Image (tube, grey):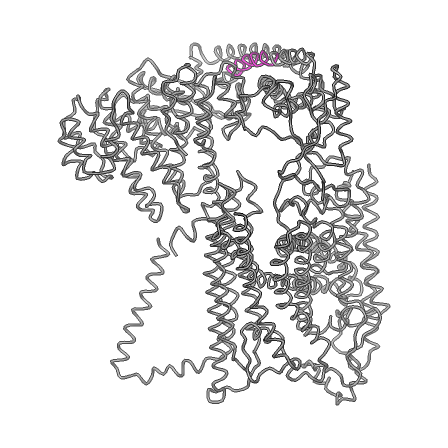
Amino acid sequence: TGLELLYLGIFVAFWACMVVVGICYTIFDLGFRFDVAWFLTETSPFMWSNLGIGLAISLSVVGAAWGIYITGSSIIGGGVKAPRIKTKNLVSIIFCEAVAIYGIIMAIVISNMAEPFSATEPKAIGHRNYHAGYSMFGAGLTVGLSNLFCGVCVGIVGSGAALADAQNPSLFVKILIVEIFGSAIGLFGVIVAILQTSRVKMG
Amino acid sequence: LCCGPKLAACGIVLSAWGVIMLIMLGIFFNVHSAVLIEDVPFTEKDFENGPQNIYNLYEQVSYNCFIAAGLYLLLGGFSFCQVRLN
Amino acid sequence: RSEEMTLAQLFLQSEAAYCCVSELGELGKVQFRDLNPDVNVFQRKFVNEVRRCEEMDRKLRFVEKEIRKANIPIMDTGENPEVPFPRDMIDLEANFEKIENELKEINTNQEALKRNFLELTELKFILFVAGVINRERIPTFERMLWRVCRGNVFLRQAEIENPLEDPVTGDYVHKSVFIIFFQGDQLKNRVKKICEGFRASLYPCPETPQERKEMASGVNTRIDDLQMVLNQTEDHRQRVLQAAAKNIRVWFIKVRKMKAIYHTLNLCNIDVTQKCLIAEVWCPVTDLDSIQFALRRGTEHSGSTVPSILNRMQTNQTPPTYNKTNKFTHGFQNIVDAYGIGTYREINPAPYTVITFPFLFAVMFGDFGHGILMTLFAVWMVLRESRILSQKHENEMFSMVFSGRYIILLMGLFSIYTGLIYNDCFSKSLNIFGSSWSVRPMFTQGNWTEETLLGSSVLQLNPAIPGVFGGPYPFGIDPIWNIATNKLTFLNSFKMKMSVILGIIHMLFGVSLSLFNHIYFKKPLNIYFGFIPEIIFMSSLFGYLVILIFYKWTAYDAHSSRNAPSLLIHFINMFLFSYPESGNAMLYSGQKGIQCFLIVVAMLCVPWMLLFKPLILRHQYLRKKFDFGDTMVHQAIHTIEYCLGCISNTASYLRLWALSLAHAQLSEVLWTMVIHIGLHVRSLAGGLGLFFIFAAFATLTVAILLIMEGLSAFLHALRLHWVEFQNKFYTGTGFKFLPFSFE
Amino acid sequence: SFFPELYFNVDNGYLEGLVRGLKAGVLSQADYLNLVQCETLEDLKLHLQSTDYGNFLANEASPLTVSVIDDKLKEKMVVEFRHMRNHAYEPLASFLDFITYSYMIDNVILLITGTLHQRSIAELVPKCHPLGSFEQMEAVNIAQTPAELYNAILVDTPLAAFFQDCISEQDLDEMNIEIIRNTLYKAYLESFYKFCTLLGGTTADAMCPILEFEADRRAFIITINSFGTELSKEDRAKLFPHCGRLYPEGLAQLARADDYEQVKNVADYYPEYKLLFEGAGSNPGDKTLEDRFFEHEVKLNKLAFLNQFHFGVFYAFVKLKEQECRNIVWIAECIAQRHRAKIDNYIPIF
């Protein structure tokens, strides 16, 4: 596969460059030019906040779409010889959208606390704004990734259940147990994203 | 015959809608004298002296609505005539 | 309930029970069910008549296929006949066999048609072998020669345009002519095998110069196709005989009728001693008189003069359900039955749905002009019902649109209303009886003058209460908000709050309605350890939020804008039980104790629905003298489902706010860059251009917001009815009536 | 985060749903229990009307005979297979073409033996399976030397990809046609195994055991049936497949067998074929070895279906469907002759 080879080439070149650069700089006693403080103090907190805000909805929507297609294709295909399964097996799609609903609510909640400031140097901004930006970025990232993996698992099991239900009517009502257990990880992601940013007082 | 009824019915309802809405929008401009809530669009980059220029210009703008209504009504009449061609 | 009793038995065997069951089927108010043994279909008392009927249907199917290949339309507008049970029917089918036999010989005359083509193909060789090959196989054919002839031979090709018919099936296929020049006979045999693989059957062997064999072939094809068009008199006879399709479509109706009659009479008991040929029937209570009238008619057609009735009986099976609709309720009952069929005596959801559906739609689609358009379409479609009903239409989309007549009507009415209540009318408010916000002459009191010189580049916020500001508009949104640049904030707040409040009352409605469902069925356990914990949980968890929203609305004035408490953070602290010492003032005094008790009752709700009722079921089973673990699993499933669906449904009710805001934004977007350009300074070209621009506006707002966003809101409200509302009182299981009525 | 879990459905979900839907259309055991109770072919027709095999015999078949049923069932099979193939994408199309190459080989061999029986030329056409048909199927009659066969088949049929180099002779007879068959079969099996293991994932897991068993069964059959031939032992060694678990056996023990007991000793070291041979008593009153081969094939095919992301469930489906066709036609033939000697010798699929 050409695309995989391209990705591997880029990745290997990147890491080889990193390793060689690091070793020569460390041997060259030039550790005073590696001042990570400047790297993580020049960056504005609002960049971290807004990246978190974008991801907190983007990744959730990606997971919702993944699960939507993965279950819908099988639901539509398997009902040709059994139209009875069209309406019985709509729970999976409902959960695949509930993921995005949680994502939107979290985006609204974190979107608050965006009062600007006037400081332009690290000594004037202070610790509080740095904490705010980092915490908001972390909350956005964790909620997005949690809901992404949640939606993927939900979609896969929804496809399995929908496909198996066409054989015997008395299957789905008990196979939906894994379907319901899918959403708990997304709920946990939302809870942690809530808790991480419960003490931000940006402004 | 020409301009068959199949689309002429749609044309007639469209013309009636056009006449009614354009007449009502013009009347809303004139009667309320173009309150900024119901009338944002205009063309004047200098009005600091007084409102009379604003009112005159908004009357000028609202005038075109009745010409549009007349054109829509003539369209409706033409479509109705084409419907009678059976 | 729908019915009181539905298992009465009033049927007895007779010598002409066929007429009895035929008239009962004509009534169209019964359903048949029997044959518990589930015997094989070819061990039946009436198998021979079913076989005969199948033979008649096969013959009839063949003749109608032949008729439809003649492209001769069939007319079916006569009366519904009565089946002639006596042996006369036999004579009729005899005639039908003769008809089929004629068709057979007609196909034998299609043998002649093949001969015609054996000469028409010949004509295409008017110009060391030659032949004819299928066009679609021309490339591959050439390939073979290049590999076997090895290029020592040569070939040339010619093409025909008009397709040549297929004698056997009648499909049109394309062909081509080829001429090969050879150098040996072994190659002639090899390419003869290849051409046997490609069907180059014909061979005009050269004998004379070009002219002589050419004219001989021409004369031959002329005589042959002349004889064919002369033999086309058989096709003429075929058309003449096919003209009798009207005399036999009535027979088709009759044949299907008697086939259904015999098939349903097959269900009767598996014995005939003492005339014990009996079939059990589902029949309602309000139509018994017509049923016994039908039995009297059946005995009238019979010469045996027997009562042909039997006494009532009752068993413990599951009766089917039938919604007795009229012109109005049908369109809305069909919408709910599309997802699930109610049990025997389930709380009918059509009477409430018929109104709460267009209301939620109108909340999702709250615009004035679009609502007016929808109601006008509704008026058009309602008033012209008689002609359209007695009319054939190719547009199936229009048929399913026409099904929802009163749906679209009520939807448009409530859409007009909600357009009036938002003060939304084509995305612009209608200042009807006054504004109360901006008074600049009063504003000059509060140090407000000369700022507008910098007004050319600033925004100059308006405050609340410099002394006479504020005030409630008596009806809807104050029009000034429509032109405010920060309208989105207040609109978002108001719409989110309205959506959440609407959603909570919908759900409590659901559960209170469920309480009726359980109390009728005489289930004290379900009321005592069911409805009560769930309603208490719902109330304690969200009625508090509703009441808090209303308190904040009716409590805090404008001067308290500093440190105005936020409800959402208080709800996060409601869930997380976290009380910081500062950062958020109490909304009202004494919130701690009430809030803590709310948390504790919310916690105490969950275990009541898990342990108690499976244990009481176990106790009842012990009193009787039941897989206990399976019951625990079911109870845990139910309780976890309800508890998580709580949060999921209250969160999913935000679709109302989402789609309402999206609709408002879309309408404003249309206003902003379609007709805005249409208004300008040109003294003469205003109306001319505006006529085109408004035509485009009308087409685009018909295409997108009128039919489409309406559909999205329609289906979203349907879903909100199917899951968030219906699953709290609606079992969604059972049978649906299958009457005995014919076509 | 691997192949079958996250992008299997984009190009296969609909088709897999259709196949698993049609799996339920295969007749069950109770269907057999009631179908063996027919009295005449009309009752068989009706009981097929009552199940998913209904509404395919609406012709005027008044003199109904079992050959008509055979033809109609085969027609239904080819129709469903063509449906499944035409809606497919490209890797799956390669898979299905790999499947159909077997029947194409069968037709090629049938026409090659038909050339020897020169008296029949056109009658071979109804004998050939339309599933394995292709553009140049009937051209095989042209060849009279195997080099001419390679010339005919090199043209546009990809079957040449399995014997373009593997056949070297210029004297077609009636004894080397079996050599042609075995060479083509082993080449096809090796190519199919290599392609399946190249695809990787659950497809390789599902298709490796089946082709392994197929190669080993071919080895066993060729070892047993080679007795009394002009071929030498080294030539018998030449025809063994190398895709099974019998790869060292192919030259070590099977290639020096002299009797059936030796083949039994070869089978004794592998339980899977040892139990198969022990159950195959081959007595007049007991089933033969071929019956056990068919039953093991059926069991493995039935096992093959259970895989949510089975890119190759079509192999199991088509094999099972052919087997149902054989069961139905055989039972109908037994019923038509008015005898009940072997009605209770049907292999119970599903």
The foreground one among C645 and C180 is: C645
Q: Is residue A31 above or below residue C319?
A: below
The foreground one among D55 and C199 is: D55
Q: The C terminus of chain C lies in which quarter of the figure? A: top right
Horizontal and vertical percent for residue B71?
Answer: 82, 55
Whether residue C605 sits left or right of residue C363 in the image: it is left
Q: Is residue B49 above or below residue C546?
A: below
Horizontal and vertical percent for residue C172?
Answer: 54, 25
Main secondary-structure element of the magenta-colored stretch: helix
Residue D124 in the magenta stretch? The answer is no
Which residues fall within the magenta stretch?
C102-118
Whether residue B83 sits left or right of residue D199 in the image: it is right
Whether residue A190 sits left or right of residue C7 in the image: it is left
Q: Is residue D43 above or below residue C389?
A: above
Which image quadrant for residue D58? Answer: top right
Horizontal and vertical percent for residue C37?
Answer: 54, 28
